[PDB]
Length: 112
Length: 215
Length: 218
Ligand SMILES: *[C@@H]1O[C@H](CO[C@@H]2O[C@@H](C)[C@@H](O)[C@@H](O)[C@@H]2O)[C@@H](O[C@@H]2O[C@H](CO)[C@@H](O)[C@H](O)[C@H]2NC(C)=O)[C@H](O)[C@H]1NC(C)=O
Ligand SMILES: *[C@@H]1O[C@H](CO[C@@H]2O[C@@H](C)[C@@H](O)[C@@H](O)[C@@H]2O)[C@@H](O[C@@H]2O[C@H](CO)[C@@H](O)[C@H](O)[C@H]2NC(C)=O)[C@H](O)[C@H]1NC(C)=O
Ligand SMILES: *[C@@H]1O[C@H](CO)[C@@H](O)[C@H](O)[C@H]1NC(C)=O
Image: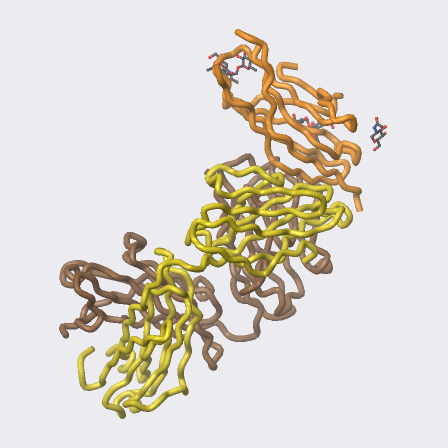
């Protein structure tokens, strides 16, 4: 049975080293058996998991009251946090399945 | 601009056109390309994000691609409504700036021809009572979007006190232009008639007004 | 959903300064990057500045030479651009936009850098008659004369009439003042029964004019 993937926004986020950067992951769940993961793409071109909801400390996920949206925040961004990020919804039942968001970019700049 | 685009692009209705955007390793080579549509008289809108994704509201006739340090916007099924300025943009990681391309004016040639409607307004009673006189020649509903305007006072050409706008697009996808002849009231009443003559594709529509005739 | 509304535009003298504002709604402002882009008449888009959600990251076009400061107040959902030492070359439409890449744009505000004087418009009717009638339709309009700076906007019947409207670009006269016209095509049968009013707004002079356009009896 088809279901839509989460969306992940904005497409590009630019911040200076030391600031925070927040993406928004949006998921229209059709039931309550799911979990949301936040990933980054490794040099290897492999998803590295950063955090999940429900629940290193620099990567935080927060579920908003609207029952759709999640804030995914890099606290105290560093230059080497620059790269490609995505979120993934995992259906837990009736069939365990992951659907990935589109990928977005973080650029973390040198403080002048 | 450090993202270079062709200044112009064109096709005819139903065809496919491509608009290129050329950059460098520090921008297009290593960063996502975004595209924008700016219709006449409006603010830009996002058309493509992340090289090739469409926001909601953008039809699938618009697509983006990127290879190396070059990117391209393709528009299939070209329509009159696509006439607009298109821009590409991307982040530059060598200068830590956002850069817009220089922009490409898209024209859609070969739309259906339409001869101009012309309305010539004499000076208003109110303006004449304020000791001024302006003839207003409004030109509408024409295609292609190019006209020539000539003014006459009883058959003689007038060039002094004429201002004319460049045609621009109407709501209904045709073109419109305006022309004004500034006169004193005395000059207005000096002649038997004045005419606004509009040439479009080698043919001419002329409208006349007279100070002694309620027009 | 998303809405962005610029203000603070208008006339400023060379060497002067101006602060633009942009009021935002319909998204979570405090975490959202916000941007200024400008566009000189007849020219391309030029990115000005972007600010992070927190305000702790700011980026600027090199060409500005640190004459501009971007800032924000998350309390009020408002973005700012302080512009100093303004030159003729800064004359442009300034757009507020959401994100570094502008997923949504405001309609922009025109900043005119000039030592010329403000002047509000005179509005004259362009009255319909048999001579502006084309069978079942007729043209009527308003002449908006002698204003400075740009822009004027025109609506009809307070925005209830938008179909058949065309408001022309301004002419710049040798006086250094602008003029434009707005025209509307309406049913010729309505000329006796429906009032038509042009609503002219000239925000640079804090002026609005509502001019009734009465038909001629000829
Ligand atoms: C869609 O999911 C929301 C959120 O569900 C919670 O968070 C998930 C990650 C998962 O852990 C769920 O088991 C959680 O319940 C559902 O929203 C809530 O629904 C319950 C029951 O009505 C309510 O008590 C909670 O307060 C709600 N939480 C929030 C934040 O809104 C929602 O019902 C799901 N929709 C469907 C169609 O099943
Ligand atoms: C960057 O974020 C940190 C962490 O904020 C917390 O985690 C976020 C994901 C979100 O859940 C916030 O609501 C949390 O507060 C900010 O530092 C915290 O700020 C609070 C409030 O000022 C303070 O009480 C805590 O002690 C701070 N925690 C730490 C670890 O320092 C920080 O201010 C943000 N930096 C910005 C916005 O520039
Ligand atoms: C990321 O960069 C920081 C310095 O900014 C460094 O301390 C850290 O080791 C880097 N990450 C790695 C290589 O794990």
